[PDB]
Image (cartoon, coloured by chain):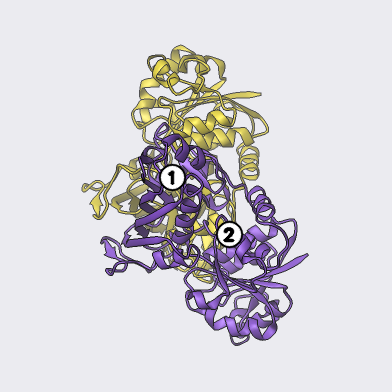
Chain colours: A purple, B yellow
Amino acid sequence: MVNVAVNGYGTIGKRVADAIIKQPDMKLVGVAKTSPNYEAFIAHRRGIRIYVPQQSIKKFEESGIPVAGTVEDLIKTSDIVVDTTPNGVGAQYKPIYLQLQRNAIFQGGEKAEVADISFSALCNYNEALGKKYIRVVSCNTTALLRTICTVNKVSKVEKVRATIVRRAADQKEVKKGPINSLVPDPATVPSHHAKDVNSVIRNLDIATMAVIAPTTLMHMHFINITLKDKVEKKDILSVLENTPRIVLISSKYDAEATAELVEVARDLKRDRNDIPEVMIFSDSIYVKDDEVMLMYAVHQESIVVPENIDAIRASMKLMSAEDSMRITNESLGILKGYLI
Amino acid sequence: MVNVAVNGYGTIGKRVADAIIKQPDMKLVGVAKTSPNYEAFIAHRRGIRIYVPQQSIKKFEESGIPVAGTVEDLIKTSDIVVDTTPNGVGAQYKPIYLQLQRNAIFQGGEKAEVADISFSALCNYNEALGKKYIRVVSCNTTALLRTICTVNKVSKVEKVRATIVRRAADQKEVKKGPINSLVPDPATVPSHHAKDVNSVIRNLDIATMAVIAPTTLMHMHFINITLKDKVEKKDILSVLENTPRIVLISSKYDAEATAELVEVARDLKRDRNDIPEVMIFSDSIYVKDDEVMLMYAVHQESIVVPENIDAIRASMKLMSAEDSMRITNESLGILKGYLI
């Protein structure tokens, strides 16, 4: 039985915690948070136990939300830590995990050196088997990796160039912009995505560009893939339509807009209206000879959730790639085929 | 039991159909819709019977979604119709419901003359008992009536002055602005809200102004009430804290922003992230002698849902105001007290 701790109960933290609870071979010990905001109140009402930095206990304890113990308390009394702390804080907790001898899963805004390997379950689960420290790649890297590794089955992927249109901040954030601007992110080519992808696929010729748009719901990727062998369209479409963690969006029901996909998720009653799957617009799938083009949407709040679950399995070597992803996929209701 | 039809499966209709499904004394006969978009797809997949206007049947059927009959058929089969069609379309169906001899509930965007009475359950259910045609007031009119009929228990409301900040368009709408403007709505005073409140509370001296902001989540109201007698804050606060369909928002958990309230709903796992209750900011409650000032948020996608359920009960004389509101409240998970 794996007793899991979650460090950092934010957008990703809260989701991983609920994913952990639905797993048959894992238990959530508790979660670490520094401020008693509404995310914490709600967590406690749901019976999730909250661990806090010793120095914040007093402050935190003024709000009435009971504290189960300190953050080291949590790490020591767990078998592995899913770290979902802010960019840069993982590396700060890294020495703590080391000292207490806990494996730990890090998020994608950390430097690669925080982990012993970087990960995406559809690409290098077997290579991650046994790693004590694993870095799950960022949300947009994950979407690129899922698409690539899946297209690669039809033919070796020789080259990737991509433009990432990033949503500015999540819907709940009220102090972040831009309100009305496009903001190169960064201006320099390439963006960090290409390298992040090279921490999982060592030798891919990848170049990416990114910009921030004044939207909160989902990112969007615009991809140009060069393959080795002239391929057929049915084959690129066959494998995109049959890969869990990837869904296709048609143009049949007038839902090709990130806001309308969010509405589809609300009406489908998905938890927190999450769509953890890569959402590829079926009408954008262009394959001519050895060239592939298409666009897809990425739901940043949830895309790495299932990856953290498999990463845990990889780290503690509980089962194969196919076994892990099959439980993760089924327990978190992950789709394949047409979303809409 | 009571067989109910829903004419217009859009933002309100999809939710009135789901609430009808949750009532112990009602059964959803089917819903009416013109276009076979993602909302119709999803209804169909849940087993909801879809009826389409005669002249749209063939285009609708190009989608492969089966059609149970015309709108007239749906009408003939129900004991009562919940009309949730676009503003002005209700008046187009009024003569059809009359000729087909079926009671009907209309939405606030219609003229008061389309019905035999306008309604809000916390104020005049008893007056609407037996009315064959009832107009449930608009979303912001409803929020003003719940607040006024509740405050009125502490001391007679003699005067209301309110400013309404309206969200531009719901989140699924991608063709409506404004993107970045404030838009008098209208520039003349008063806006229609005051007349609509007066269709419910006939002699109240009320004036309202409204403006459109570039937000999609919720409306906000800023109100000034003049009472007959001087009162104590504790008495205003105590009624506001103990009335279903009204919730209080504290400043304890950092959630005083409409986007953070949407977030609270997501994490509380409310259906569609709906918050049908009037959300009064408890730090806003200002009581001095006979003057009360406060501000609140209104979730426009859902506030009228419970109201339409009670309206069915009033029109069909099914049970008392209190009995109906208790079933509507319990079954739809309506709250009172502090939300956060």
Amino acid at circle 2:
Glu
Mark sitting earlier along the chain (1/2): 1
Q: Would you call the spot at circle 2 few (<14 residues within 10 Å), some (14-19), or many (20 or more)?
A: many
Query: Which residue in the rendered view is the most extreme toward the front?
Result: A229
Task: Please tell me whether mark 2 sits on a helix, a strand or a loop.
Answer: helix
**Residue shown at 35% from the left, 58% from the top:** A164
Question: Picture quarter containing residue A216?
Answer: bottom left
Same chain for the residues at labels 1 and 2, yes or no? Answer: yes
Q: Which residue is mark 1?
A: A280
Q: Position of residue A288 (x, y in %)?
A: 34, 40
Q: Which numbered circle lies on residue A307? A: 2
Q: Position of residue B78 (x, y in %)?
A: 56, 19
* C-alpha span from label 1 to label 2: 19 Å
Q: Quadrant of the N terminus of chain A?
A: bottom right
Q: Which mark is residue B322?
A: none
Whole-percent x, y for residue B2 in the image: 62, 24
In this rendering, the answer to whether B116 lies above or below B161 is above
Q: Looking at this rendering, what residue extends furthest in the top direction?
A: B99
Determine whether the residue tagged by mark 1 lies in a helix, strand or loop. strand
Residue A231 in view (yes/no): yes
Q: Could you tell me residue B268's position as x and y percent?
A: 59, 56
Chain letter of disc 1? A
Please state if A104 lies on the left or on the right of A148 as rendered.
right
* Quarter of the rendering containing residue A58: bottom right
Seen at 54% across and 78% down, the residue is: A114
The vertical placement of B2 against A55, above or below, is above
Tell me: A319 left or right of B150.
Answer: right
